[PDB]
Length: 221
Ligand SMILES: CCNC(=N)NC(=O)Nc1c(CC)cccc1CC
Ligand SMILES: CCNC(=N)NC(=O)Nc1c(CC)cccc1CC
Ligand SMILES: [Mg+2]
Ligand SMILES: [Mg+2]
Ligand SMILES: [Mg+2]
Image (tube, rainbow, N blue to C red; front, side, top):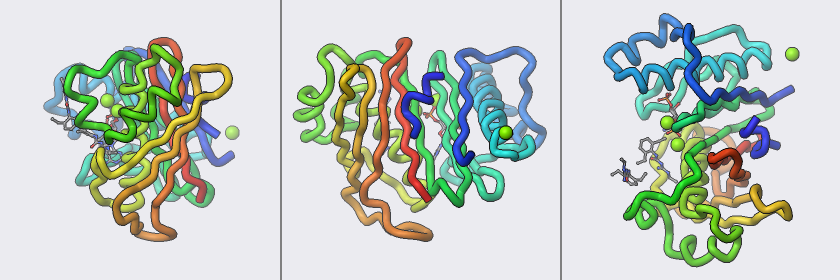
């Protein structure tokens, strides 16, 4: 799988690269997409099937994944996880809450960002440092964005608060083999959480493979 390259029972994952015919949403999920265009219906159904395949590995019966007030997925009792969908990719990573405090994942096409988007998602220090820490010709702007998204998705279930693109400063390293590596997101705002210690540093991994960027953060419980 692509997502295994960015991950460290207590943790499980599943991914698909298309929308298989014959998948349906669970009844509890169906209203959430009753009025949605086909592309949205399909990604929603497929990514939630991935989540249930992952939850099944952790011993959890098939269950609906509803959405909270800020769109965040609602996991079965005792579980945490993250979802992502982009062109050519649907993925889920889930964890047992006793061992895994939070998960955030993201996938994007490995393309340059559209003009004007980089300034909206980066800090000036990231634009200055990432060219020095990443292999030439990779789309470090898109990889940075992918890491910002994983950072938010791991942050929000623990804080239930906004995190802006300027509120996390992300430093990157590259592995010797050149298409994977580590990142560290440092939170620049108050990181108080609903329980447990505050969020200040979140360590993740990135990977470029088959035209996709994958990023993931798994915070130990
Ligand atoms: C066809 C889509 N084209 C885009 N340019 N979409 C964005 O810019 N969205 C966005 C916004 C909302 C305007 C605010 C901050 C940062 C971003 C980038 C994720
Ligand atoms: C480091 C901080 N990163 C974020 N705050 N990222 C988001 O807000 N991303 C997002 C956007 C971007 C404008 C639109 C719709 C839904 C989502 C959440 C998956
Ligand atoms: Mg088993
Ligand atoms: Mg998506
Ligand atoms: Mg995303």
